[PDB]
Image (tube, rainbow, N blue to C red; front, side, top):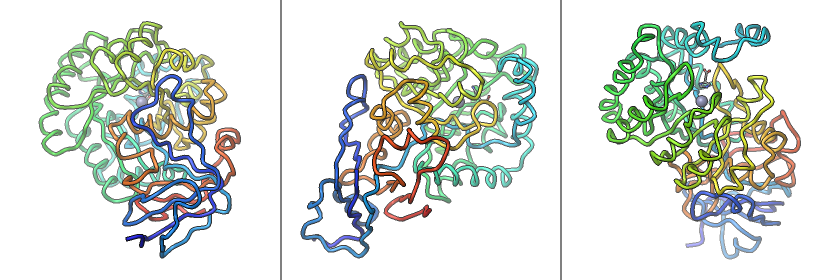
Length: 414
Ligand SMILES: O=C(O)CC1=NCN=C1
Ligand SMILES: [Zn+2]
């Protein structure tokens, strides 16, 4: 019967992002915009979302007047390292002094610095710290996010990070996708035996699988870290073990991480700053989603961003993320990422919106559950303090959120 819980009326602009799959190449530009719209919600799910009139015959218990505001699905942040101990502010001077990201790491700092902190922090402290950051992420519009482990580089801590991720997911509104990234860096105890280290991380997959602590396996394929050869062997093992594949590829040096991702049919390849044309073609060919992290580029103090236009021109499905982490991108503001995407990745507003909703969702195996406002989907949406979708990435560095809804309930009210 047409008796539902909630209905949003007088929506100035509604972006349903309705799609039948990830958006690649030209389809990323095809943004469907509905003026003067409405959204019907019942039992935490979307009943209807479209032109004014669709609410005809319906009786709702709660009518939300959006005052001509912009409404879109809740945002998806497909790549973060949410759970971590300590912070790296004391490393700012090293970067200012011109020491490269990799040289800091080779010095025993960077990821290895955060590893010490994360290993030392209690499970309760990590949970408390992550809740704060995750709620801030929520306040900026993120209702679904991917979170990677990778600051343990040992059985105890990696497992602790995954358990924390599980707690967070079950104790607050943001839905989380967990990724095991024990292969983030080479810990001191394995400096001269990286392959053995990788095997130790692989030995953790069975129990991680049994306890459902992670759905994907990631790795940092980079100079001074893991080679393409080691990454292939590791990822193939991960796939046999039943995990989806992700990879931090061609972030700094052009090693061919992208090509490997495509060959292994990874769900996504992330960073891709130094990816070759062959890598771009391989990504498009395999349907591997290219998750760009313009925040990390900007934060590293660099001027060369990933070649997003070339990727889109070549048929790649592009996505974006904060890469929220203490070392190279300490920001929860996915909206700023949208702005950076426009100004430095040279993406259009349309492409950007598809990037943080539909493509972000598919990049983490949630293509059928998030990023779209259509019948059956969980009622996850954002009512913005803006009249149109171009305004969001246009006005930068702030929070444009008016209200955030998760499962049909307002969880953020500004
Ligand atoms: O530096 C960090 O903590 C995070 C990072 N991993 C790979 N690139 C950046
Ligand atoms: Zn990352």
